[PDB]
Picture (cartoon, rainbow, N blue to C red):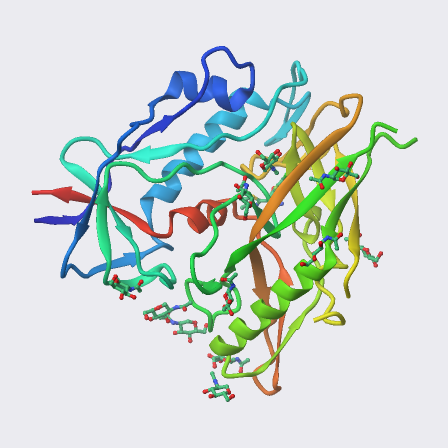
Length: 340
Ligand SMILES: Cc1nc([C@H](CN)NC(=O)c2ccc(-c3ccc(Cl)c(F)c3)[nH]2)sc1CO
Ligand SMILES: *[C@@H]1O[C@H](CO)[C@@H](O)[C@H](O)[C@H]1NC(C)=O
Ligand SMILES: *[C@@H]1O[C@H](CO)[C@@H](O)[C@H](O)[C@H]1NC(C)=O
Ligand SMILES: *[C@@H]1O[C@H](CO)[C@@H](O)[C@H](O)[C@H]1NC(C)=O
Ligand SMILES: *[C@@H]1O[C@H](CO)[C@@H](O)[C@H](O)[C@H]1NC(C)=O
Ligand SMILES: *[C@@H]1O[C@H](CO)[C@@H](O)[C@H](O)[C@H]1NC(C)=O
Ligand SMILES: *[C@@H]1O[C@H](CO)[C@@H](O)[C@H](O)[C@H]1NC(C)=O
Ligand SMILES: *[C@@H]1O[C@H](CO)[C@@H](O)[C@H](O)[C@H]1NC(C)=O
Ligand SMILES: *[C@@H]1O[C@H](CO)[C@@H](O)[C@H](O)[C@H]1NC(C)=O
Ligand SMILES: *[C@@H]1O[C@H](CO)[C@@H](O)[C@H](O)[C@H]1NC(C)=O
Ligand SMILES: *[C@@H]1O[C@H](CO)[C@@H](O)[C@H](O)[C@H]1NC(C)=O
Ligand SMILES: *[C@@H]1O[C@H](CO)[C@@H](O)[C@H](O)[C@H]1NC(C)=O
C-alpha cells in the first residue's frame, strides 16, 4: 500500500569523468551511474490520479538545472538586484545529456502508461519504476527541443484550457527537425534556422485539428506573439553555449495550413534576461567557426488570446518562458509515492 508523497530524489546518468562538457562535469559530481537492467512492475487493476501541474519532481529538476547553469555558464557581468558582478566568462563545451530522476528507499515512482494521457486525472495502466527515463535539460522558449514524442495522437496539455492565462503544451507525435547555423563565413552574430516546410505545415495542420477537438470545433488561428520580452517573442535556446534568438513568424502563419525550406532569421545574443529569474546578464561573444545545432521539435508552447468568446475563432501564439513547463512536458507521467 502507498500514498502520494514528496522526498528528495537523486539523479543517475551516463556522464563521462574525462569529458570537459559541463553537463558531464556536473553529473559526475552530482549523479550516480545508471542501472543497466532497471525494474518496472506493471500494476494490474490499479487506478491512480496524476496531476502534472502540481508535481514536486518538476521543482527538483528545476533546482538541478539552475545548479548546473550556475556552475557551468557564467556571464561576464551579472545585473542582479542593484549590484554589479564582473567575473570570468570563459567559453565552454556545452551539449545536454539525459538525466534520470530516482527515488530512495521506502519510495517508488508510479508511471502512467495510458497512451493518450493528458497529464491530469486517473490513469488505468500504471507501473512502478525506480527512475524516470533520461531527460535532457533543454532550456528553450516557444518550441520544445530534443524531448520525447507522444506515442499515439498529438496531446494537448493545460492546467485549465478554459483559462487563457494557463500555458498550453502541445506534445507532438512526429519530430520536425530544425537546423540552426551561425556560418563560419560578416556579422558574427547573424545566424538562421532551416526547417522543412512540408513537414512543419503538415504537423501544424494536425495540431489545428486536435485543438478543434478541445474547443468545440471553433476556427483555429495561429499568430506570432503580440508583446512580451525578447526571450518569448523569439524562439530562444542555447546552442553549444551560445544563446540563439530566432524569429518564428514564418512558422506561425495560417496561410500554408507551402513546401520548401523555411529559413528563420536568428541572432546570437550576449545580453540575456536570465530564465532563472535573477535579472539580466552579459555573456561572452561567439566562438569562431561554424556553430550548428540540429534539433528535434517535439513540442510547442502556446498561449491563447482572451476575449474571443463571442466569435467563432480561437487564436494561439507561441509562448513559454516558465522553464518548469519544459520539465513538465517530460515529467507529466510520473509521481512519487511512499510505500507503507
Ligand atoms: C518572475 C520571473 N520573470 C522572469 C523574466 C521576465 N523578464 N523571464 C526571463 O528572464 C526568461 C524566461 C525565459 C528566458 C530564456 C532566456 C534564454 C534562453 Cl536560451 C531561453 F530559452 C529562455 N528568460 S523569470 C521569472 C521567474 O520565473
Ligand atoms: C491500457 O492497456 C490496455 C491493455 O494493454 C489497452 O487496451 C488500453 O488501450 C490501455 N489504455 C491506454 C489509455 O493506453
Ligand atoms: C530525433 O528524432 C528521431 C526520430 O523522431 C530520433 O530517432 C532521434 O533519436 C531524435 N533525437 C533526439 C531526440 O535527440
Ligand atoms: C499523430 O496524431 C494524429 C492525431 O492527433 C494522428 O492523426 C496521426 O496519425 C498521428 N501521426 C503519427 C505519425 O502517429
Ligand atoms: C484531461 O483529462 C481529464 C480526465 O479525463 C479531464 O478532466 C481534463 O479536462 C483533461 N484536460 C485536458 C487539458 O485535456
Ligand atoms: C478554469 O478557468 C475558468 C476560466 O478562467 C474558470 O471559470 C474555471 O473555474 C477554472 N476551472 C477550475 C477547475 O479551476
Ligand atoms: C544543416 O544545414 C547546413 C547548411 O546551413 C548543412 O550544411 C547541414 O548538412 C544541415 N544538416 C542537416 C542534418 O540537415
Ligand atoms: C522535406 O519533407 C518532405 C515531406 O515528406 C520530404 O519528402 C522531403 O524529402 C524533405 N526534404 C526536402 C523537401 O528537401
Ligand atoms: C466537430 O464536428 C464533428 C462533425 O464532423 C462532430 O462529430 C464533433 O462532435 C464536433 N466536435 C466538437 C468538439 O464540437
Ligand atoms: C519577425 O519578422 C517579421 C517579418 O520579417 C517582422 O515583421 C517582426 O517584427 C519580427 N519579429 C521580431 C520580434 O522582431
Ligand atoms: C539536440 O540533440 C542533438 C543531437 O544530440 C544535438 O546535436 C543538438 O545540439 C541538440 N539541440 C539542443 C538545442 O540542445
Ligand atoms: C470567456 O469564456 C469563459 C469560459 O466560457 C468565461 O469563464 C469567461 O467569463 C468569458 N470571458 C468574458 C470576458 O466574457
